[PDB]
Image 1 (cartoon, chains in turn green, purple):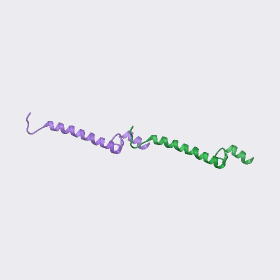
Image 2 (cartoon, rainbow over the protein chains, first blue to last red):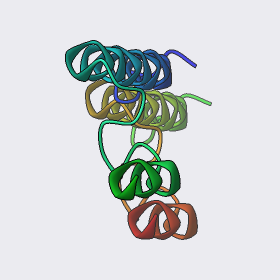
Image 3 (cartoon, chains in turn red, green):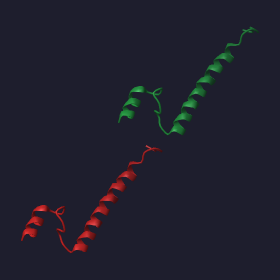
Length: 53
Length: 53
């Protein structure tokens, strides 16, 4: 299919790039705080345990 | 037959030329629109499915 209107391969490469940027942003946060769970979004149970403790 | 009032062979050649011209126009639409089904005139069911999707 030599489509002129649609290009699924660029879509696949873009979603893969977005996932790579997500992991890189996670590592950037993880280096900033120096903490594996910097907030409740990281994992709420151990986060609340650490807060009360 | 040498009938001066009529020439059926030119009529048949004109019919063939008209069919070749109509095929050239539909290919012209396929080239500029970039789609094999760009309107309801082409195929209405798949076109309506494409519009809804």
